Image 1: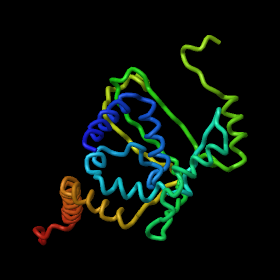
Image 2: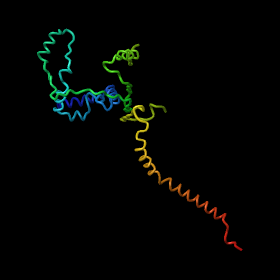
Image 3: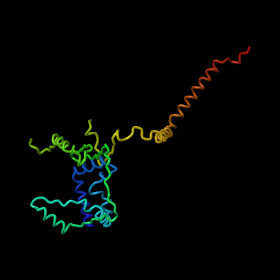
Image 4: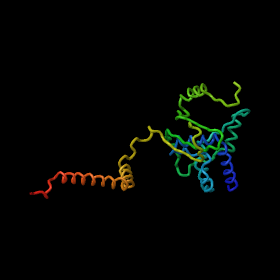
Length: 160
Length: 77
């Protein structure tokens, strides 16, 4: 745990050494502020330093339940063999919440806002502008992907 | 000249929200009144003494002018 704490601090330094991930996290923070969607995946450095084994075990016993897990195989895999292997090894993961309490996902409020991290020593500027998306199961996702395909993407190495 | 090369600013993060998300008059009185009396108290002792001595000179000049137009009681005879 201590060695991986050193490793995750070093990888946090490598992550904010990169620049598009910083704008990614800033955009999520300013978009979903006040909600659990603003906070980053790797978390803050104070949480890195104060996280202990008891909280990790609580998270593992709280969010690694069977009905929120998918064992997905693709390629040269035979479905009955995969099913009996899951029955042999991976059956009965927890099956119990040990409190009769399943956590729920509250809706996240999107706030129109802006965050500006000015640091002029960097040679290039990264700007991300977004609006609220529809969701995973919304039928308009395909249409919005069509519009994003129309607008597109480009970098300085494209030969078009 | 234009935006882009006005100043060199580093490590400064600005957070702002949309005008439609926030209010145009957020606590306009409960915070406006302490603010306006704060500003009045801070800048009241540099304007009020000159203005009140202007008022005193104005009323003294008017009073002395009216006594100047008043009759002299020296010349009874």
